[PDB]
Image 1 (cartoon, rainbow over the protein chains, first blue to last red):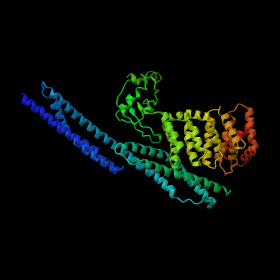
Image 2 (cartoon, chains in turn orange, yellow; image 1 turned 60 degrees about the vertical axis):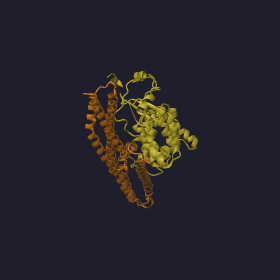
Image 3 (spheres, rainbow over the protein chains, first blue to last red; image 1 turned 120 degrees about the vertical axis):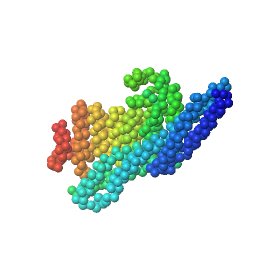
Image 4 (spheres, rainbow over the protein chains, first blue to last red; image 1 turned 90 degrees about the vertical axis):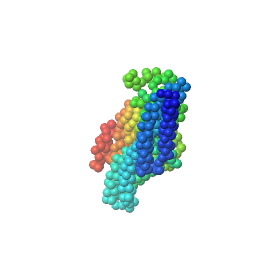
Length: 230
Length: 307
């Protein structure tokens, strides 16, 4: 081999390690700077489009990492021992790549689960608010200003409405849990001035209770008014 | 067999998924108090050391900071021979009691509505709750709130009494039963229906608490200035209007309170106190009119057969 060619190989190993290491460091700086525009499906999948671009960038560096490990395990053995320090730096850079790749996988995983949860949020919210708007727009005359047949007719309608309310009460529980999980996975991506889906949970729960209480009061008023017609 | 956290500091905002996804490993340790900080930093969890405890993975058992070798002998099963760090039940029920004693308006309403779910989906919270005067809390808010706040409190309470420990807690808490009898005089027909059927599950769970019920009614009658049982018979006199339904619940309650009592001397005591108020006139008057529904009629003749 030769001391000249040995040092020229050792130095090539240093060169490739410094070059590869800063390329990986660049990828991880870019990862941290991605963030998230809004807690919406369009914004989340823009975040994921960017993570996937960077995943492909790390992939293009896999073969360089692997050639680098090659060089490091085949380095000449000097009396100095300096090959051992350069090998340790190279093993570091390889672990850096594995860590960066794991980071990207974790971000992509949490994007996936936020996307499933946003889907579930809009499906549950549609179910609930259309039930709530349906009852919320139907007329409600004063029970005091109603005839006996009309009281009977409206009371029957309000039992149907109550039974549907009882049925979707599970959906109310499901959407509360979905919002809780959405906060958890969303805080991993960005710091939010105000908690992202906590306002939303409170608003939907508040509407649901308002319409339930209103409908229950209306029901008992219908019954009291009906009692006066004997 | 491996360790993981769950952030449950706010019980009104539990995330559901334990992290990390791929559990870090630790396998042995044998006192636990001194050993929990090592794992709390192994995880770097946003959970206050202090107020932390460890729960076994499939079973849910919360470890006593004692021995691994004694909790061993308590309980793992066969798998070991081939785990979540979270907040103490103490600390979580304290946050619950805090929220209830310190909030108002819309927050309060939301929280009471959530209690049902919180207790339903973490069953083990209910005993510690009873241990922390949680019932005193519920009543001491409910006795001052409108019928809507009260109906949420009652849904939570019925959830508690589905569990044996919650049932025993109310068997200890006289104020609860007193409040339910007071609630049989509510102007909300929903609140009355709910209070009554809670009083029914209360007297149906055991038999020894028929006397507990009869005493609660006597105690409230004495404080309030009214005759004993005025709320039940007031419901019987359909002053709000017809309610076959409420009547059936009320009469079945008075029936199985009678049928579960050895004292014929206390039984004649209570049946006097109530035919005094018009019970027999009501019974015959309902037994006549054929608008009476079969369920109800069946139970009124049960009363009369007792007499």
